[PDB]
Amino acid sequence: LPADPKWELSRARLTLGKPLGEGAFGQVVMAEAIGIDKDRAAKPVTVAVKMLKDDATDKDLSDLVSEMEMMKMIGKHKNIINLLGACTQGGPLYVLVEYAAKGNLREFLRARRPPGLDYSFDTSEQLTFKDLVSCAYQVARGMEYLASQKCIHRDLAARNVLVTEDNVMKIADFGLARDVHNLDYYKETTNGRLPVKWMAPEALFDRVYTHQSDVWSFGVLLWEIFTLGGSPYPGIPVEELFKLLKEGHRMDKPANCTHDLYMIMRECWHAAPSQRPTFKQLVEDLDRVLTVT
Ligand SMILES: Nc1ncnc2c1ncn2[C@@H]1O[C@H](COP(=O)(O)OP(=O)(O)CP(=O)(O)O)[C@@H](O)[C@H]1O
Ligand SMILES: [Mg+2]
Ligand SMILES: [Mg+2]
Image: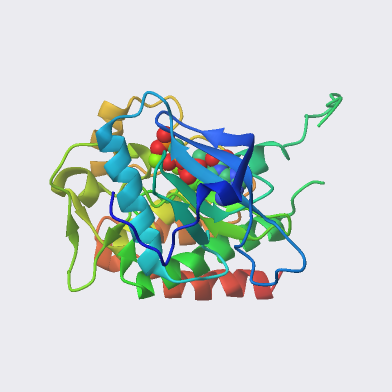
């Protein structure tokens, strides 16, 4: 594994801590990192360390490397999870990223659903319409930046948006992200995980991804936000989801969602990718919704 001194942090500077979250092949743990902050007086930075699980393969490893490399070219933005460094030498690969205290967006929204009339929870503030639109607006801003970096995310979803102590949204998980520089589109040529319920039709059969296929995913994300962590196309087998999408089926309007937002959501889900709004447009339309509320 080739060294990159620019990003390398020696693992002796790193003390591993409590678990943050995980999935099938990767896990993320809290840690303390010494030397990240240039102010030497007050220290050490709390970071999140992403690493492979024990049953992970060589393929999982090269995917985590690619993920790390993608974050290197991206550039820093308020609404994008920050790469802080990496331990690539003499030990397991650790990818160091900015710590988001409030976990992922899906779990953040779910923990704020009300109990229902006549019921109370017993042990752990309600979100407003404005809070939720804010969430949408912040992600749209980060995606707008991401597209200007000529990078497509391909896995935009509530489970991949993080929340800081200040309720700032940070897009995370660049596992499927691709460099689209000097490309009109990206064409998938392998087999690997696909986030089916978040994928535009054209991505699902032509295996063709653009910024516009990311916008489709944002639309699904919108639906997640306004159902406070709902799971897309509930009760629908995947094999059929796709005939349904062809036939012009789209998800119904969530109960919290206003008409204006559902139209925004619906525009993202246009059959023709050229008729979906750009992220820049999405930032505009969501700023408006927010300016007059
Ligand atoms: N910087 C961070 N700060 C706090 N928590 C984080 C974090 N990064 C990730 N997490 C937590 O770990 C979970 C999984 O993160 P991530 O999406 O990066 O891994 P992953 O989806 O690639 C695992 P797999 O590929 O095995 O399915 C997140 O949903 C979140 O709960
Ligand atoms: Mg993820
Ligand atoms: Mg992953």
